[PDB]
Amino acid sequence: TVLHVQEIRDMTPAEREAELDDLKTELLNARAVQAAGGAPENPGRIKELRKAIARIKTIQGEEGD
Amino acid sequence: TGAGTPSQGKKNTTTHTKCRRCGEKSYHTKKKVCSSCGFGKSAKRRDYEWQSKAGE
Amino acid sequence: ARSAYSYIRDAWENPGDGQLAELQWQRQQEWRNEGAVERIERPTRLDKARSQGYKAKQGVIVARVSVRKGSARKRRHKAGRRSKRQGVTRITRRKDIQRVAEERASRTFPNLRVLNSYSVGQDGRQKWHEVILIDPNHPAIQNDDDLSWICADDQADRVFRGLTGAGRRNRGLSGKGKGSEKTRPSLRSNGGKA
Amino acid sequence: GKKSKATKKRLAKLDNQNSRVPAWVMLKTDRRNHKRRHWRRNDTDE
Amino acid sequence: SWDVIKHPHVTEKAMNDMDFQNKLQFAVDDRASKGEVADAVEEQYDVTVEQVNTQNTMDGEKKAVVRLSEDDDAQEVASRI
RNA sequence: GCUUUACUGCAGGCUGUCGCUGAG
RNA sequence: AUACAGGGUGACAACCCCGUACUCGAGACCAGUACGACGUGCGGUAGUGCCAGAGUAGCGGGGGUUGGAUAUCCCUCGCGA
RNA sequence: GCACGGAGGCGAAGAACCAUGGAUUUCCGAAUGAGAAUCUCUAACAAUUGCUUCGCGCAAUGAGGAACCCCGAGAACUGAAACAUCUCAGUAUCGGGAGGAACAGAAAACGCAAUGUGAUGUCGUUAGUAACCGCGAGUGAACGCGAUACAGCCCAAACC
Ligand SMILES: [Cl-]
Ligand SMILES: [Cl-]
Ligand SMILES: [K+]
Ligand SMILES: [Mg+2]
Ligand SMILES: [Mg+2]
Ligand SMILES: [Mg+2]
Ligand SMILES: [Mg+2]
Ligand SMILES: [Mg+2]
Ligand SMILES: [Mg+2]
Ligand SMILES: [Mg+2]
Ligand SMILES: [Mg+2]
Ligand SMILES: [Mg+2]
Ligand SMILES: [Mg+2]
Ligand code: NA
Ligand code: NA
Ligand code: NA
Ligand code: NA
Ligand code: NA
Ligand code: NA
Ligand code: NA
Ligand code: NA
Ligand code: NA
Ligand code: NA
Ligand code: NA
Ligand code: NA
Ligand code: NA
Ligand SMILES: [Sr+2]
Ligand SMILES: [Sr+2]
Ligand SMILES: [Sr+2]
Ligand SMILES: [Sr+2]
Ligand SMILES: [Sr+2]
Ligand SMILES: [Sr+2]
Ligand SMILES: [Sr+2]
Ligand SMILES: [Sr+2]
Ligand SMILES: [Sr+2]
Ligand SMILES: [Sr+2]
């Protein structure tokens, strides 16, 4: 969603990795808030984050990093 | 001592266990052989034509 | 004129006479001390090998195999049998010893395929045969006009399916007419009565 | 007995499967866990 | 590639360990060693891990009890997630 | 299932012969 | 209507919807085949006993197998052009 | 998604869905560094082979598949109104092995004996004929012919 394939391909290798760590962290924090039974959730993102990370990982392999 | 009920109380040995290769609880942990898929006995998978009707 | 090969040939028509006799008497002493399957650099009966397809080239291998002499090594019936199916001593197997030899050789060299084989004598308790095997994966062979045919997929494990010369003879496929009613095109298709 | 790590993972799974069919599935399908097991009445594998 | 830290294990018992012993509890990958749990934690929240105790749970996961140095305050670390 | 000088066979043992097997 | 096969749709539907006839497109198999082309070179006369696959052909002892009977195929022991 | 909920989200930056191609693809598993009931211990084609730069450097094998196919091992109940040869049957079942099909196959053939046919499967027929057989019960072809499809070649040696 918020993150599109073009944007990803437009990132330098270093940017994708920095973007990767960033996404992984939001996810981890979502899973933390979920572990605490936290309700200020937005279930749609926890799902988007995973796809985003899969996209960046797919793009990284494609471009050769 | 009767061969029936009184003798069943002595059964607390573990023999057949979940098999690493096929998943069936048929891996004899003392023989280290699966009575279902043959693991531990043969590289090929345990099979027999008598497991079905002859013309089928 | 006569080829040098014909002399090897003529010598082997009577392995019990002349120099050959002495060679065998000497050789077998060593063979008896060797294993079941010994790879050898050169054929003992060159004329025969070349005649059967052998070539001094990469991917061509020769191995001598020995097998115990005699009839079947069968275990007597442990369950009920009518007199007819109680025999044990005079029962012989349906595969000749040369075929058993070709199979053992091929087992030893899983990647090679049996091309042909021939006899190199025997003593009172065993028989020896040399087997020509070919490497279907070696380019020297994949490029040979005379041997590349053996590289085809349907030639894999040919010895185990009776496709050898010894295999075909033993299956009663020599004759093209009378007597081959139950052998051709296969023993199995004819109900196994050949 | 003494359970290995793998045995333990398997026992854990069996424990998890041994749960109720969520109520919302009831509504969604407008109307039963056939694999419900009891530690006493039943016998697991291995 | 599997990550070490899965998520914080938050329960009454976990909170006590956090308020009374400066310990944090995590659900972690069961292939992770005590050392790998120590590093991962120091690198995720920038703290000094003093000790790590582990347990393979009946939930199929591995639980880690991480005690931070007196320099760090668990209550506060956990409070930012 | 069991027995035996029931019928018929089969292992096994003994024995001769041929091959292994040569020189005087 | 070159479409009256079949199904769906709140009841018996060619004409309400999917389809169906007609026409058209793509993939797979036929097949790396057929055809075509490159190269190679078929064949005939006379002379020459130069070459042409051995435990083989064949025989005997013992077995199995076969419709194979004297006249099947095979194994085994021995002999052997 | 099945799946007719709640909440939330994605889609005109053309999502869903479909086709083709690609990415990712934990552990055990032929399972191959060693071991192990799917885990563990300290760089690995384990094992058997071929080639070999003689170094696992380059390669092969292993296991699966509904049956079909090829090569081996091979019963008994049953029939004969008993039963031993015979039958059931080269069946059931077992060992090994290949393919998309296998196997066979260009005559030391046939022998409607001929001034004739012309690789091989297979189908129809020849025929329950010839042949076998306590000549009992039973077992049982082939050549040929009509079809299907057609296709013929390569070595060893001589001489170099
Ligand atoms: Cl082979
Ligand atoms: Cl004719
Ligand atoms: K019988
Ligand atoms: Mg040539
Ligand atoms: Mg519970
Ligand atoms: Mg512990
Ligand atoms: Mg019989
Ligand atoms: Mg392993
Ligand atoms: Mg009877
Ligand atoms: Mg056939
Ligand atoms: Mg009678
Ligand atoms: Mg018969
Ligand atoms: Mg005939
Ligand atoms: Na082989
Ligand atoms: Na129980
Ligand atoms: Na969890
Ligand atoms: Na009885
Ligand atoms: Na026969
Ligand atoms: Na004989
Ligand atoms: Na996949
Ligand atoms: Na390999
Ligand atoms: Na090597
Ligand atoms: Na009767
Ligand atoms: Na009777
Ligand atoms: Na008879
Ligand atoms: Na005629
Ligand atoms: Sr007693
Ligand atoms: Sr009692
Ligand atoms: Sr006990
Ligand atoms: Sr074993
Ligand atoms: Sr089997
Ligand atoms: Sr193979
Ligand atoms: Sr009980
Ligand atoms: Sr629990
Ligand atoms: Sr010839
Ligand atoms: Sr023709």
Image (tube, coloured by chain):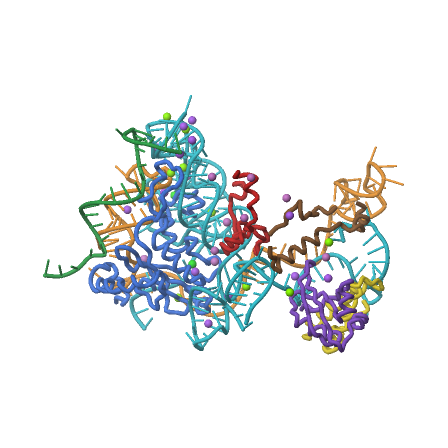
Chain colours: A yellow, B red, C blue, D brown, E purple, F green, G orange, H cyan
**Location of residue A44 (image quadrant):** bottom right
**Residue for point 70% across, 74% down:** E50
Task: Identify the image quadrant of the C terminus of chain B.
Answer: top right
Q: Residue H114, how many percent across, how many down?
A: 33, 43
Q: Residue C28, how many percent across, how many down?
A: 27, 62
Whether residue G75 is situated above or below residue H38 in the rendered picture: above
Q: Looking at this view, is H114 or E38 the one in front?
A: E38
Q: Does residue B37 appear left or right of residue C132 in this picture?
A: right
Whether residue C185 is situated above or below residue H131 in the rendered picture: below
Using the rendered image of the protein, determine whether residue C69 is visible from the camera's viewpoint. yes
Whether residue D27 is situated above or below residue C23 in the rendered picture: above
Q: Looking at this view, is G76 or C164 the one in front?
A: G76
Using the rendered image of the protein, determine whether residue A58 is visible from the camera's viewpoint. no
Q: Does residue H55 appear left or right of residue E31 in this picture?
A: left
Q: Looking at this view, is H159 or C192 the one in front?
A: C192
Q: Residue C161, how many percent across, how many down?
A: 43, 53
Q: Looking at this view, is E44 or C69 the one in front?
A: E44
Whether residue H117 is situated above or below residue H8 in the rendered picture: above
**Residue for point 23% across, 59% down:** C14
**Residue for point 34% across, 36% down:** C83
Q: How many marks?
A: 0
**Location of residue A15 (image quadrant):** bottom right
Query: Where's ligand 9: which quadrant?
Result: top left
